[PDB]
Length: 116
Length: 151
Length: 70
RNA sequence: AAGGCGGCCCCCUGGACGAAGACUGACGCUCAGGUGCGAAAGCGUGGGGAGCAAACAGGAUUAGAUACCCUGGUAGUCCACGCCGUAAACGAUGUCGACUUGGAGGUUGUGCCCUUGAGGCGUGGCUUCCGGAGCUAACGCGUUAAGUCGACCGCCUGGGGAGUACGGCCGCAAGGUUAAAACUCAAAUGAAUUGACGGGGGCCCGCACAAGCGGUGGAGCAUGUGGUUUAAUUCGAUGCA
Ligand SMILES: [Mg+2]
Ligand SMILES: [Mg+2]
Ligand SMILES: [Mg+2]
Ligand SMILES: [Mg+2]
Ligand SMILES: [Mg+2]
Ligand SMILES: [Mg+2]
Ligand SMILES: [Mg+2]
Ligand SMILES: [Mg+2]
Ligand SMILES: [Mg+2]
Ligand SMILES: [Mg+2]
Ligand SMILES: [Mg+2]
Ligand SMILES: [Mg+2]
Ligand SMILES: [Mg+2]
Ligand SMILES: [Mg+2]
Ligand SMILES: [Mg+2]
Ligand SMILES: [Mg+2]
Ligand SMILES: [Mg+2]
Ligand SMILES: [Mg+2]
Ligand SMILES: [Mg+2]
Ligand SMILES: [Mg+2]
Ligand SMILES: [Mg+2]
Image (cartoon, rainbow over all chains, first blue to last red; front, side, top):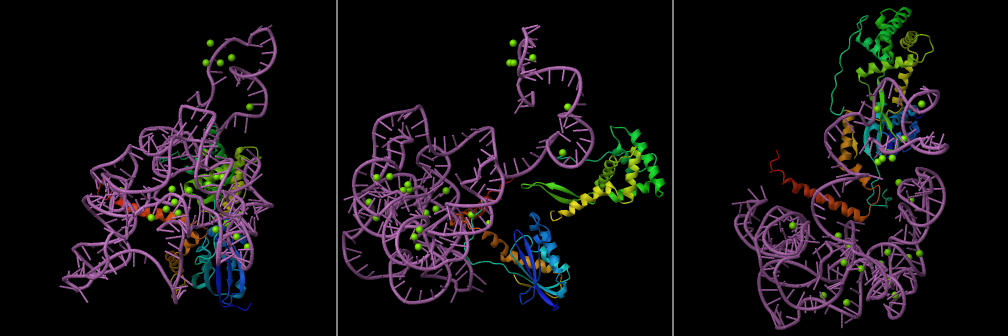
């Protein structure tokens, strides 16, 4: 519905999982899909290929909106940081730009302890 | 072999048909080290399979292998608490030998009378794309795509 | 690390340009070093060894660039 | 000066160094008792509390796990004013002067040429690394000495008992400082060497793993051993070996 012509793709990668959310420039979600949500529960949801499977799933189920242009905003340096956007173009999108947004503080809050 | 590269000694192509591939079949099937019983069982079983369905005695038996060859197989590497299998391709030389073994081990599990009869039935199913041989090939294929994220 | 895909070209080269941006701008490494908090002593100690062994490599080079080996 | 000090701006303030000269003219060095500053944790009275997080609770691993791991979480960490006065407060190296071959650097001034444009020639102040004589138990230090010397101060006299007990002084408290004895042992210790070992690191091996085939442990029997019985059940071999 509303046949949105161009959209945005947020990749929220992490050391444990990957979430793909497709939006528009207004910041309103259309569909989401995660590696853990794609049946890869366990230690396999952090694999780079596990992000490949999820990216196609979110590329699908937004075909109702007829999205033809995507802007990729990668976040959260982790395993699924570049593979998950190889699958985005394989779904037929015409990526206009790729931007890396990620929280880099200027020495803000104190991080947790070292692990032992 | 830590430091050894091997070359397998050649074997005699079989007299009846001249296929060295079939000569391996009698070697795999042979038990307790004797070829007189094993060779005749293979030859006799091939007659029934050829008579039952299609000509080209060798080609009917070659169709079965074309259906049971596995194109991928997992191997395990231990890292932490538990080992996880990693898929890897199968070299064509070992690919022939793997399905060549699976048919015989599956044949010895039928309830028929003669080992020749059990071998003929199993080869019939494999050529018809059915039976225990392709089922064994199906598991290694399914369990290699089950965890393909590893490499 | 903003990249603007040029007139067509291949997406792989655009991806390879985006990867080079993160490598050159140090986006990947800063997240790892700031994931946990290490004490100020450990920061001072690690920089001590890092500079000492860097200079020791230079001082150990002069003992092999002129001495015949075989 | 040490503890320590890290966005930018403002206004109060201390110290260091360099060039060229004037000026006072021994005004100097060290310092028992004193006096001041002194990380973090901790204490008191007010505030503030985002994030981390002693204590605490739950989930796991475990034979137990009052721990490491996971999800939460209060004092505290922050501010103002007072206490506390201890640290591996460590270049384990007191302060102040003099002299004694060298290299490669870092940082901050300067006075000459070639303001030829980079540069070249030197002199100053801090500071990093390597090494000569020499030093010594050896490691190592080596003009910023652990070298050759002068002037003051502090400290040491086998290991435990013990920086503990009692008694003073200090503190709101925690505790700090000064500081023994009986008894007990023939050692305690520093450096370096040869091995052995490591859930330290390399490189190379082999039926060591991997790829396969056939077995043992399940049954009946043969044979040896342990045990138990017996008048005796002769003696020896006992992880691999
Ligand atoms: Mg964590
Ligand atoms: Mg005094
Ligand atoms: Mg404090
Ligand atoms: Mg308080
Ligand atoms: Mg309070
Ligand atoms: Mg915790
Ligand atoms: Mg002390
Ligand atoms: Mg104490
Ligand atoms: Mg200190
Ligand atoms: Mg220090
Ligand atoms: Mg001391
Ligand atoms: Mg003094
Ligand atoms: Mg030296
Ligand atoms: Mg005391
Ligand atoms: Mg006392
Ligand atoms: Mg094996
Ligand atoms: Mg048995
Ligand atoms: Mg004897
Ligand atoms: Mg005996
Ligand atoms: Mg004996
Ligand atoms: Mg004996």
